[PDB]
Image (cartoon, rainbow over all chains, first blue to last red; front, side):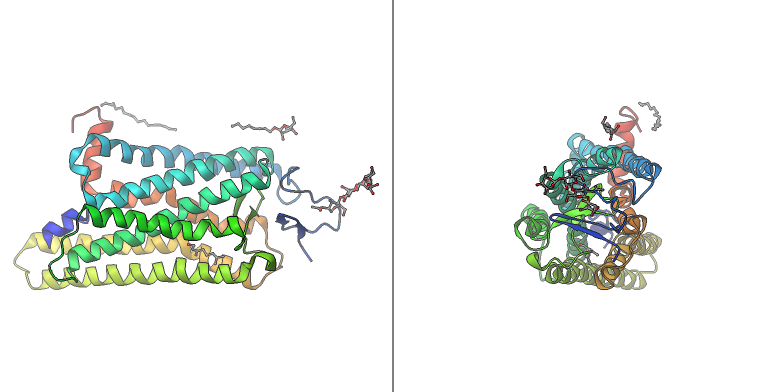
Amino acid sequence: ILENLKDVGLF
Amino acid sequence: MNGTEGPNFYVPFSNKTGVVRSPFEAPQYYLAEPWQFSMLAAYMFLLIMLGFPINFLTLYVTVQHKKLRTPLNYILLNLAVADLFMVFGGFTTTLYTSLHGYFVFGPTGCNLEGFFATLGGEIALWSLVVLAIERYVVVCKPMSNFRFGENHAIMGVAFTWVMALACAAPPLVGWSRYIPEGMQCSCGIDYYTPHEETNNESFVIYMFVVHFIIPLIVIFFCYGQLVFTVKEAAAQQQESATTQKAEKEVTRMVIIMVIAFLICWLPYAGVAFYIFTHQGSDFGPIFMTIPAFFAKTSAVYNPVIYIMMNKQFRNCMVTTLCCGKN
Ligand SMILES: *[C@H]1O[C@H](CO)[C@@H](O[C@@H]2O[C@H](CO)[C@@H](O[C@@H]3O[C@H](CO)[C@@H](O)[C@H](O[C@@H]4O[C@H](CO)[C@@H](O)[C@H](O)[C@@H]4O)[C@@H]3O)[C@H](O)[C@H]2NC(C)=O)[C@H](O)[C@H]1NC(C)=O
Ligand SMILES: CCCCCCCCO[C@@H]1O[C@H](CO)[C@@H](O)[C@H](O)[C@H]1O
Ligand SMILES: CC(C)=CCC/C(C)=C\CO
């Protein structure tokens, strides 16, 4: 999920 | 009886002394002392001085930084544009009218300032819904083998405009109406009079259900599923300290976004619901603008939460503001 959390600007 | 009616307005002040005037024609210093109009002008100045640079800089750094022009960022740019509609279509007009003591642009300018102020707030409203849907679709992967692309991002922005037009156009064509509110210096949807000629009641209900309940349920479900997905993944991967930090940060942001959303629209929900239900009462024009305070300020703190607290945007803005190096 770490990559998708960066795409959406949450991590 | 504690109000004065006209063909296109409703001043919340009794005319038993004969001093009430049209909010389109004469200052309203009988419902508020002149200094309160100056403080109203002072607050509009604050929203302009803070809301314009933070929202304009968001559009500026996107032009300069290629890594910001991704489809998942379209709705954030749509949020900055909506805040600018609130700044120029509403805040600047109200700063001007409050300095006069009344709405000088008349009923036509009332529909104009009311259409763009409602449009700006609704686009920002539905941008926060669409952003939650996309973050839920991308992270929770609820659909089988789906990748979010540019065409899905454009439809997400177009969906916000359609929902906003489905919310600001009806008052211009006879479903509800735009009239000066509170201190009569800014215009908005009529929920203080039961104007049966334009069916104010069925619109306020449609306003509450479709444009507040539906957005609130969608935001809670999407971000609820997201926090569940993230906590589940981290629990199944406690050997990764980075995944444990991400779960905390994602949870902390979801709480901030949901609480900020409530602070924005819940006072405007209940207070306008009370003014609508317990109608015709002795509403203080100062009490009218208590919900408008929290909602209008979202033009400033939505960029802080959704842009400045985004690592990719904050780094590009520090680079741009610091002349090109940081
Ligand atoms: C609540 O507060 C006020 C009282 O209810 C009200 O203001 C009054 O409005 C009326 C008009 O609707 C004003 O009437 C004019 O008064 C002047 C001087 O007294 C007259 O000269 C004038 O003559 C009229 O016009 C023509 C003659 O040329 C003729 O066709 C008319 O028949 C008539 O003769 C009017 O009589 C009145 O002065 C106003 N009073 C004050 C104290 O302002 C407010 O409008 C009302 N507030 C709201 C928001 O409606
Ligand atoms: C940012 C610029 C705002 C312009 C402020 C407009 C001031 C309103 O000027 C108006 O002129 C009338 C006739 O002279 C007077 O009754 C009052 O001074 C005032 O209501
Ligand atoms: C209940 C009313 C007159 C307006 C509701 C405004 C709101 C809480 C959200 C609008 O999108």
